[PDB]
Amino acid sequence: DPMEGREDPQLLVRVRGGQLRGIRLKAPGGPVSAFLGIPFAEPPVGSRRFMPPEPKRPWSGVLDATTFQNVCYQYVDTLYPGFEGTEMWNPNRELSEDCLYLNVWTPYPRPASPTPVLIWIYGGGFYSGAASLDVYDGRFLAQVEGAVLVSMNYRVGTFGFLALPGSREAPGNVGLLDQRLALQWVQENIAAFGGDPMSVTLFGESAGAASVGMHILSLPSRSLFHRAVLQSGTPNGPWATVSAGEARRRATLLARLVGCPNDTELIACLRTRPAQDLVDHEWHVLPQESIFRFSFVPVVDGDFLSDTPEALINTGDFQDLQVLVGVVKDEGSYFLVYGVPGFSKDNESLISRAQFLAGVRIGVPQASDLAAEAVVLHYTDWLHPEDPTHLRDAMSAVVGDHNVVCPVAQLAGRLAAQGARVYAYIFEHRASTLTWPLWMGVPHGYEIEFIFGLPLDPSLNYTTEERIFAQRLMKYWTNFARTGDPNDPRDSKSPQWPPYTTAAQQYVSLNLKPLEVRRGLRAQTCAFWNRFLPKLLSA
Amino acid sequence: EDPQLLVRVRGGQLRGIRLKAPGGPVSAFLGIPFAEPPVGSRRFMPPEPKRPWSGVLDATTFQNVCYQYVDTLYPGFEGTEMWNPNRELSEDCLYLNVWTPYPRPASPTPVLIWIYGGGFYSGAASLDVYDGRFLAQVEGAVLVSMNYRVGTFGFLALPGSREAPGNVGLLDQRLALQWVQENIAAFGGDPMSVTLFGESAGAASVGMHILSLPSRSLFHRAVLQSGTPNGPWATVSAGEARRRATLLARLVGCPNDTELIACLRTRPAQDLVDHEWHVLPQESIFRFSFVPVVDGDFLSDTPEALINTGDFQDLQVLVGVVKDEGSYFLVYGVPGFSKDNESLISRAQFLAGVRIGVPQASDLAAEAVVLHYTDWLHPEDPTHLRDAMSAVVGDHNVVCPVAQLAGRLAAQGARVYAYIFEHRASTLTWPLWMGVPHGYEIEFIFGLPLDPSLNYTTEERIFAQRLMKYWTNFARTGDPNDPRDSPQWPPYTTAAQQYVSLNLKPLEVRRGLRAQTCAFWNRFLPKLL
């Protein structure tokens, strides 16, 4: 670079591919280094669509790493024009298939000694999301905790997860392979930023959490990280994976919907289609009317996933693993306004008993008549079986328990029973700035802004208590990243966060009040979902 | 010659006896015959009215107990012996008892008629716990209790046959009812104010009188304590009754219905008793061999159907349960349970126990029961498992059938009051883990704690007086609340599901009688049994 000598010497870094120049960003407490839009793969475009990522080839000169890159091609929610509750999750950069870039935040100047690395994997149902969203801003953890934080884009929707299992051209799970390639990039290069490749903690929410779980369950990924955090998502459960037959079914149907016919010719025809056509048709291939079900998700391929996640967590040895797992207070509430008759964000969504039964059929699409009746039985308040408020809240609880809370309880149980050190939480604080109605409680995904420390930015109008709270959570998360223990070794005054064990089943509540220890994560109910009901899910 | 002790009934003259109650004297007329003795060829047959007699019939003493199995699980133990026959066994047993105030009531008095329980195989009106002198003296009530045939003698049935039609124990009860209608006024009783009350099998009996049209002109109100005509144990089908009768016949060497029954009538009573427990279809508890049969006569249909389609608009009903309905029965057949230790069982024993307590359960149903009653925070804790086993039996056999009955009756016009009885007698000889077992509210209802020699506590005496007041208020008005007065006891309704707790503390109103769990038993599980 001819202008290197006139520029900030503290923002120049070399990695395997070549030289990069980052940017000095302002965090409330001081500056941070950001290296944004670093390519970790060759653009998965044209003939590379549906294919595993190829490592980015070295470049000449100085790569401009000062701004976020393109967002992977995806559906954009336009249900509520101008509504913050949806818009804050929408892409904030141009959509492109050329999207395999990652981002790095570090202290400014960069750390002098090797520093624990946090790697964020975003959620969004495997059909959406971006590492560039404001809610995933790494600057606060970097400045306040001194963390090195990395986040990557990975392909979503058909581009990431359309599969014709067994084929060469569309093997499936390539979004997960994008994630893995980013993990390898970190292993080779993070030391140049002052990061410690021997202390890497994965964390993610929802589909990002399911992703993290799948890296736990896939051997080639295991040498690429040391600890994991799963927020409101699991590799097990009803939505995070499909079987090979179902993947093939869905891919074939989509292909027919966009006008395409041997796997090779089908896939080639698909590769001739515009990205937006694939996006425009991906939602028409689900087998039933449903919520919290996504068309193109990880597939049990016998490769990346050697078996079903339930099998793998049932037979796995997790002795050298420390994991942090948890849920928010109202996991199911959000999804109700997206397909259950009678629900809306703009009224109180008080429903009738008929609407509750129908809603149970939509939320548990695999339930036989008997299974559905059993769910209705368990969740009805038989003292007030017609009360619209109880029915609304019960609908929410059915969806949240089925898709998140009980799969999390199941995971935590299996991991703890088979060697892993497990910490469990429930997140119960509702953001003062939330624009979703009060009846939705603490919805899916609204702990994230507190983990990343956004309330520390005064311009965002959080309360003082919320700033303190955020600082607490940042401390828990980075403590866990550093030591595999969220507790402060110096702070014996504060209540301790005990490990989750099958014997005591202890977890903690995260809210404005000090840590409270509780026992049994929805134990009766999750026994219902995880032990009794699985036989009967067939319709 | 005490004229207060000489009474003329339709059959002739009776001489009673003056008894001492704590507050004063009462008149007792004990061992009054109300039927021809059901002996010889009258075995298994409907009762015939007692023929008139000459002179003055001695009614100063309890008559014989109807022939029945005697419990020998714990010989000499009060907890069991207080339920055993306290007079001689005889098939010559169809007698009733009357308690009245001394002197005989000036104006017509509400009548309370007790029907004892004991699984339709046992029981007697002469037991100390059914002593009517306290209610008669304190509340001024006229109390009647009758002996009725039990076991094979009262319920062995060959449906369709002339000689053993079934339900003749219920017919014994009915004949005693019609006797009260014809004769009770001579004792100062009001035949237009008659209240049936009974516990367990007695409660189920009361229920069946509610559901049998000819019984309905013979009473006006009913109390069902820890039992119901609906449910898994109170009735059998005609086919199953016939099966059990034929098997019992086989076991005693008998041999066409006529000749089978003839041969059965040749057998000594103790033969039949000796073999009655060998005809149950499965290993079980809270199941009894010879019980009321759905005959299409006394019971025109199943009790479930009848409570579902019945019109109960002019009926007032008091129903309830005790805190631990299931506990007593565990020591009578569930491995790992005993009165002499704390019965801390294992999980395997819990599953097996569930198979015994819910014998009709498919594997799926049993797994569902295990799932529902397991404390998944402590799935192996012996104490939890034991208490859970108790709850499974109590809920399946009593609590949830009671909830269903109360709900149906309420929904279809009846005035219903409901309770849960939660006080453990200070004198109870069963172990503490059994809590408030099946049947241990009776002694308080009958007012036994008012006898200082039985050494109950002062508070228990006050409690007994409260309950006697509730029951006789209900008998008098169809409302347990004091007609003038203390939180009010609200009627049970399907919408609010209110019931009260009966204990040393003042009335507390609660809502929903094990609502989730009884929804599980009454709505979900029946398909899978």
Image (cartoon, coloured by chain):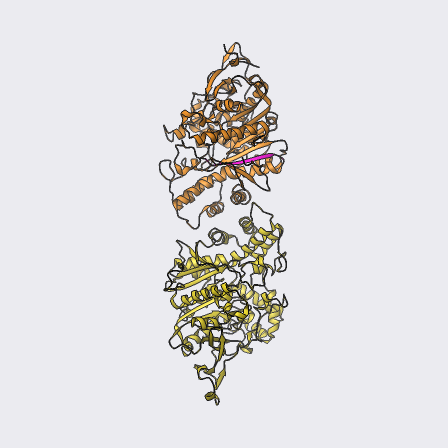
Chain colours: A yellow, B orange
**Residue in the image at 61% along x and 75% along y:** A274
Question: In the rendering, at what x and y percent does residue A156 appear?
Answer: 54, 70
Asked whether B472 or A415 is in front, the reply is B472
- Quarter of the image for residue A487 reads bottom left
Asked whether B450 or B217 is in front, the reply is B450
The magenta-colored residue range is B413-424
Question: In the rendering, at what x and y percent does residue A173 appear?
Answer: 50, 69
Q: Going by the picture, which residue comes out furthest to the front? A: A464
Question: In the rendering, at what x and y percent does residue B416 appear?
Answer: 58, 35
Would you place residue A456 above or below residue B282 in this image?
A: below
**Residue in the image at 45% along x and 64% along y:** A472
Residue B246 visible in rendering: no
Which of the image's four quarters has the C terminus of chain A? bottom right
Residue B421 inside the magenta-drawn segment: yes
Residue B395 visible in rendering: yes
Asked whether A492 or B438 is in front, the reply is A492
Asked whether B319 or B401 is in front, the reply is B319
